[PDB]
Image (cartoon, coloured by chain):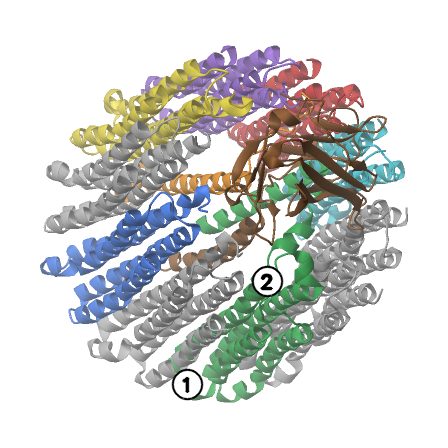
Chain colours: C cyan, D red, E purple, F yellow, H blue, J brown, K green, L orange
Amino acid sequence: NNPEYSSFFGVMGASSAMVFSAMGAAYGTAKSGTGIAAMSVMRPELIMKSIIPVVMAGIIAIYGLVVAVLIANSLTDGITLYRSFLQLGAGLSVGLSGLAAGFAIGIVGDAGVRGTAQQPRLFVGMILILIFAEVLGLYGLIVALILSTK
Amino acid sequence: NNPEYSSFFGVMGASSAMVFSAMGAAYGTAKSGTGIAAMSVMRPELIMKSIIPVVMAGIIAIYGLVVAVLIANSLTDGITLYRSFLQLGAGLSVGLSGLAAGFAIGIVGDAGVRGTAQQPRLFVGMILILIFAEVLGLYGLIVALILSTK
Amino acid sequence: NNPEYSSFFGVMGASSAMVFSAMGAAYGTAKSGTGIAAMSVMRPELIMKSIIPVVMAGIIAIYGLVVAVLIANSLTDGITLYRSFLQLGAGLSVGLSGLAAGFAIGIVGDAGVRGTAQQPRLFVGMILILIFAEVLGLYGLIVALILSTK
Amino acid sequence: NNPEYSSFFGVMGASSAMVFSAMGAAYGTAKSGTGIAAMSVMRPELIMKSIIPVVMAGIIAIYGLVVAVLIANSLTDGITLYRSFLQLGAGLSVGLSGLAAGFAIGIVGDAGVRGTAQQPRLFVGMILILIFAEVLGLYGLIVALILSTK
Amino acid sequence: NNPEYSSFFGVMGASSAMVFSAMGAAYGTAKSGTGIAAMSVMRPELIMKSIIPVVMAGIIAIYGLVVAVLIANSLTDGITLYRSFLQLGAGLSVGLSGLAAGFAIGIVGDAGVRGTAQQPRLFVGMILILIFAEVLGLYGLIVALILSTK
Amino acid sequence: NNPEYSSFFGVMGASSAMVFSAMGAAYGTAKSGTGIAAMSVMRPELIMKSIIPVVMAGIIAIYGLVVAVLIANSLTDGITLYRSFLQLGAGLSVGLSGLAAGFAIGIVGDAGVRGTAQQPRLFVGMILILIFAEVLGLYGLIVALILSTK
Amino acid sequence: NNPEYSSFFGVMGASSAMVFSAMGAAYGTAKSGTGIAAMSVMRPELIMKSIIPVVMAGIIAIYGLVVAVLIANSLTDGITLYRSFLQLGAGLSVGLSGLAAGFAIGIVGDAGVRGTAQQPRLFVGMILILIFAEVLGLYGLIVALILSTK
Amino acid sequence: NNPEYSSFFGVMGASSAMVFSAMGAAYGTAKSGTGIAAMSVMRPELIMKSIIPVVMAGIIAIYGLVVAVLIANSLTDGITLYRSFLQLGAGLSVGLSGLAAGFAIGIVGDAGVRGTAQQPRLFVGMILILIFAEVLGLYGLIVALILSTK
Amino acid sequence: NNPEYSSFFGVMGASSAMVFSAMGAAYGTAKSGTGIAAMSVMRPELIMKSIIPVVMAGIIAIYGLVVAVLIANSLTDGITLYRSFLQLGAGLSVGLSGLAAGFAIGIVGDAGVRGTAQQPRLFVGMILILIFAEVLGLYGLIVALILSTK
Amino acid sequence: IHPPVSYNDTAPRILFWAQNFSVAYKDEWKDLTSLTFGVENLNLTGSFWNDSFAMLSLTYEPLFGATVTFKFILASRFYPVSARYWFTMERLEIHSNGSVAHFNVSQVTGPSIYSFHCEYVSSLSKKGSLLVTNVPSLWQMTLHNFQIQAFNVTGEQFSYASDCAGFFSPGIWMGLLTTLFMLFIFTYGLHMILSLKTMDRFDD
Amino acid sequence: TGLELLYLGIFVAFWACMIVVGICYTIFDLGFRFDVAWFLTETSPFMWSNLGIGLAISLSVVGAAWGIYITGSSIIGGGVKAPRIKTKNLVSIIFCEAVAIYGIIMAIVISNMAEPFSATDPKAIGHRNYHAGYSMFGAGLTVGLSNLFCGVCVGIVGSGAALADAQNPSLFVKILIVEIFGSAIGLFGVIVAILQTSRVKMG
Amino acid sequence: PYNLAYKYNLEYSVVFNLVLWIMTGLALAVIITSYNIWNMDPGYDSIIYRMT
């Protein structure tokens, strides 16, 4: 006696998990990329030490993919309303966490890589701040998997 | 038999895939194209190298098209509401993901083309950033494939 | 017995707790990071000690996470609507209170580091105001825990 | 007897009491922090003496916490819809009163600390305006308390 | 009859009565304080007498308090829907009226105190204008009183 | 019999009659006062005459009070829905008319006093214009009285 | 017998009728007044001639008043929905048309007066354009009268 | 058989036919009048010949009047929904077409008159452009009339 | 047999067909005429050649007119919902197409007229481009006719 | 306010009410409210109840030269879309002298645990025409403030009621979609037209 | 920012209403009232099909015209000092117009899909018929927006192309590759629309 | 008595939509007119710089 409309929420959980994490990663890549492009004209040797934020946005994206794929695997044609809402919760948690964490990663990377261009000592501060940002996506992942697996 | 209105969400799934993928590809193409046009007058020797980002945007478009075709073939007038929701999920997953990817490709391509116009050594880093940006849409394509095939 | 949609608000609480507090932490991280990268140029010796705002901001995310997981383990299939409402309340409390806190930390730290670049004495007042900012997230945790436990 | 959803308005009252007070306090602390940081440059001997506005923002937060805690403590399951409404009323009262107070404290301080930096005489004036702004949150607390008791 | 949702309107009335008056007082105090801070640097000797517009904002706040307390005193579980509606009406009457008075007092003070700093004579005329601005809230209070006791 | 919720529109009529008239008078008072300060700084002697526009805004406040009080005295529990809607019409008619009149009086007062400082003989045209602006609120009142007493 | 709620549309016709007409008139008076004030500082001899646009706006006000009085007088507690709707139509037709005429009168009055000070020959054309502006409100009144009487 | 509420859409046909054509004529006269005023200060002898654009805006108004009056004449009580909708259609067709036409008239008249002041020969071209815009209002009238009579 | 409201959609189709085309034409003529005046002041001898863009705007208006009257002809009382929506489709098809075509013709016309003013060689280019915009209006008209004559 | 008609089986099981209940045959109207409600002599013979089905057979002896009866035929069942048991009034069956007539019913539906209400459940066009036929019929029926509940009954009380009075209707929804997609276009056009501007200067 | 503030305000109000109404319906148990199925079923398939076609043509035309003027402004301005431009860079205009060409092709193709019903009851209308409605609406929406976006893209890149050509004759023939890729997106939209309508039948 | 449902009218849909949308249009018209006047340029540019 499982409503057929209930399964929609699980699909939406998977979608959200993918899409919002994707938007966060996209912005994070974007701002860090413009920063890198600006920096590279003056200090090309910093390209590889400065791409790291893009990798971290990529990690936000992989977090989104992991949660979304897990939700998809858990989905079923007669999925219960309770479990489906759990999957929606996981999807929103991870997706919006990734959105926020990516916003942070992008802004931090932009400002930082620019900062290093004029002052190389800042590199350590960059990497610290960037990981502190990525930790938000980690928390999103944590909560998302807990809900998706309950 | 399945409810009469069921197929609506599957139709929307196909449409969303193609349409949002097209939005992403269009923005990426246009942004990279304005960058390319501005760069051409300055450093004409770099045009055929600088094209690549438009190819990445086209890759996002292809990602959209593949999913859209899959949903179109899977679609019929009597699908279960569950599969209809899943088709919509696949469509949105690839589509919005491609949109985010497209903004990424456009911005990164523009900034990087502008940089390389001034400093050739940025080129390879730009390629790497572009790859990481399209990878965002690739994740959406993976999740969409899974949702649709399930 | 209990309405089947009750679980929706429980999962909404679980999500909200993490997501909104995470947005606050993200904004704080971003503003403080830009401030750090700015101040580093003139006074590169202060970066590590001056990271304390990002260190403090991550705490809002910790708070969000704890409330989220507590709502999660409290969730089950048959919760009464009363309990689901308490879970929603706890989630919203910690999340949005942490968002307010995060705006506070972001602004205060961003201003404080830049000021300290010109006046090292400010650091102590910066810490004081930052504590007065984190306590907002803390109070949200207190109310959220009380609600979720009831 | 009572409709089973009556506690929704109680939990919403709690969430309002905490969250809106938190927003007000956050705005107050943020603007006061900008003021302190700005004034610090040429008058660092005023830092420790100028924290008062942030303290008042903290008191905003304290009213928020107090009302929310009372609300939560008094939430019983079969709460009469009547008292549940009254309780939404108390929460809104304290919370939005705290937001108004937060606007007041923040705007007052951001200018008042600067004015003091140029002119020591103002300090007493600023504290007077701050207390008059503070009593706004105080009135909100009074009203919320009477509705919660009632 | 007396539907179980009746008291909601009266409760919202109390909330409005306090909250909108509080917002008005907040803005009035904020602007008047900003003007006072601006003036003090030039003419510190005016502070004791120039504070008055903030007191006028406080009067608006007091109006809000009085109407709110009357409403709260009047509430009751078996409140008739007509009494609840009168209570709501009184609440809006006082609250939004006070908000208008707050806007007026605030703008007027911001201008007038600055002017007085540059011209001693303006003081009394400013006071008259503030008297009229508060008179608006006084009308609001009277209307709310009549509605409440009707 | 008339449905119980009918008196809603009468109570709203009274509340709006006060509130919107209040908003209009507040705005007019505001702009007039700013202009008065500005003119007074240079030409203090002209204050006593220049205050007049604020008085005429107080007239709008009076209109609002009169109509609101009339409606309040007319309110009854067994009020016919038709009479209730009449009272709502009257309340809106006075209130938003006073809003228009306050707008006009405010802009005219500002501009006119500002000019008057430079050319005293403008006073005649100014006064005439404010008359023309106040008769708008007078018309609002006439319509409101007809509607309410009908 | 007719549906009781019909009264609403008649009262709304009255309210709209007076309100939009009044707002248009207010705009017309206000901008014309700004023009007059700016003009006077130079050419005080043109005050009585320049007042004309404000009168022309007062004409819109009078039109609104006329239709509104007709509507209010014609309302009855047993009004048919046909007649009530018709009254609404009359109200909209005069009021919004008068608002358009109000913007026209105000803008042209301002511009024309300012020019006239610079060039008195403009005055005749300014009259003609003023008349053309008002005939809009006259058409609105005609339509509204026909509607209100049918 | 003639749903009771049918009169509404005929009434709106009337109201639109008036109001939207009126707004179009108003914008036309407004912008053209600003242009006339601007040109006057330089080229007085053109003033009388320059007013044609305002005339054509008035013709937009007269189109509105013709359609609205015909519509009102056709508003019988027991109107069928068919004719009521045709009546609305006529209303919108004239009103919005006239709105667009009046916008065109205003912009073109402004441009044309100020150009003519600089260069007389533009006069015929301006008249031609005004005609080609005015035919838009003419088509609005033609479609509205057809819809109304059919 | 057929629902009584069926005619509304056909009426909306006709009204849209007129109105959107009219607005497109209005924008086109306004922009074009502005450019014509600007070129005129310097080059009186190009008016007759330059007017063409306004003529093509007239063409799009005519397209709207023909489609609209064709729909009006088919607006019969016993209109089946099928035919009604066919007419709505015709309406939108011509209408939005014409609005876009008007934008294109207007902007291209302004740009081209200004260019011709300096460079006579461009005139043929102007016309050649403009035809490619106007053929869009032809396209919308064609599809609208096919729909209406389905 | 008269009491509802109730069919009982160890307890009330089917419940029906209206403020006014009337019928016509050959356009000659007659009123049934008093003869129906509260009066004990209302013959319910032939009425039948099932957890899946219900048939309420009201009866009046002299009406229209016949011992007339009205069978309201209702059912309930599981719809897989949602866990709920929905209910519907399928048809109305008039029984007349040696004769029967069938009316299909359009919009009387809802969750089985809630009653249903409607103003003017009647065959006349002017009043909603919720009862319908393909064949033109001698019969007219009108039920003003009709309310009914044939499943999950509990004592004399009705359950909470769903109502015909939705915030929208099919026609209204289609109209709102149409007007919204007109308004999108209109706002786009008006935005662009309002962004039109005029130059402040001219060349030499 | 007047009108944009208005759009933002109305948008916020609409979605606030949606959110609050959703919470209230769920809390009051009105999922039976809020059943999307009734909306989707009683909204006539004709409305879907015909909004579909109208958008299919009109959005395509919007893209075409938008891109057209975006590139035409540049083509003209550059041509002022570079008369060679007018004949050459017109390929931007032609590629913009191809979008509206697609618009017609799919619009008329879909128009061949429509047929009446002579049925009102949803059961009588049937799955095939409701599917026809939604499918036509979706195919129209898809083609319309893919064309819109292709058009804006091609217009922008063409503007850039003309401006670049103004400074150097030789570059245009190479930049046009970006234009080709832009048109490819519209072609993808066309393909998707074709597939969506390929198995549709009203009647 | 007997938990009779509240007597919603038959034309509730149409009356409700008429009220809602008419009031929405009215409220928006009022708000926009107020906005436009609120931002009405006071136009004393010849005086502003003497005052300031």
Report the side of F52 relative to D38 (left or right): left
- Give SS at disc 1: helix
- Mark 2 is surrounded, within 10 Å at the Cα level, by few (under 14), some (14 to 19) or many (20 or more) other residues, namely many
The mark that comes first in sequence, 2 or 1, is: 2
Report the side of J57 relative to K186 (left or right): right
What residue lies at 88% left-to-right and 40% top-to-bottom?
C77
Asked if K196 appears above or below H46 in the picture, the reply is below
Inspect the image, locate mark 1, and give the three-letter code of the amino acid beneath it.
Answer: Lys
What mark, if any, has residue F140 been given in the picture?
A: none
Mark 2 vs mark 1: give the one in front. Answer: 2
Frontmost residue, H60 versus D145: H60
What mark, if any, has residue K86 been given in the picture?
A: 1
Quadrant of the frame with the C terminus of chain D: top right
Q: Tell me the CA gap for discs 2 and 1.
A: 43 Å
Frontmost residue, J33 versus H147: J33
- Give SS at disc 2: helix
* Residue H81 x/y as whole percent: 43, 50
* Residue E22 x/y as whole percent: 55, 23
Q: Which residue is mark 2?
A: K48
Q: Is residue E109 visible?
A: no
- Mark 1 is surrounded, within 10 Å at the Cα level, by few (under 14), some (14 to 19) or many (20 or more) other residues, namely many
* Residue H93 x/y as whole percent: 36, 58
Report the side of F92 relative to F104 (left or right): right
Asked if J153 appears above or below E54 in the picture, the reply is below
Asked if J8 appears above or below C16 in the picture, the reply is above
Q: Are marks 2 and 1 on the same chain?
A: yes
Asked if F143 appears above or below F79 in the picture, the reply is below
* Callout 2: chain: K
